[PDB]
Length: 277
Ligand SMILES: [Zn+2]
Image (cartoon, rainbow, N blue to C red; front, side, top):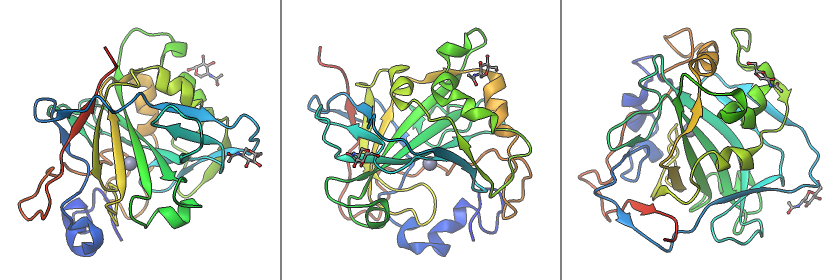
């Protein structure tokens, strides 16, 4: 059992209840510190692309700790090298947000928390045949982090919810765990075009929920996409699972981890990318 809000099973306890691997020293999230990071001009623009002959349905579930969009197999991919040859295949996208607008993200950028951080989770299909083979194996995963920020004046079509197609209206108080519903597909290419896909932090870290496996290649884009207060409050209408002390889902984020805890046996480095100038 784990939770965010029950002090007994909360994130401070994960290093004990899930020693493998929540006690490790390559954990996530971290503070993404622009001044400490190393600019690496070899890190290219990220591309997200779709298999246009895929027809299966997309679904979303309230799994008790987030809203998680589950994509069909063989449908959405990420390329980090400009070639569209299916090296990373997207599995799911879920979200982390706050009870209030000034927190919610798991990563910080120079100490700053955003209201909502989305995680697009993919597996390295280049090496592994399926999500379930990759999820617990070395180097199996790569996650994209997308920061969202609230604006007062904006057309719907300009907000991230256009790419999400409003999650087909499923974000409301009656979307109780562990219900899942079919939704219109998420246009992840459009979502990525709402920010600068060349401008990101990059490091090796972990899943941010138990068992915190250290096999995640992280990419966190620096520019946020935009949403309204109305849209953030939609997520806040979801109920938490019954493991949680709080009724309404919010503050479902793990606290910050150090880039290099004192016990590390080989330091990791935080890299940054920017467009070819
Ligand atoms: Zn996440």
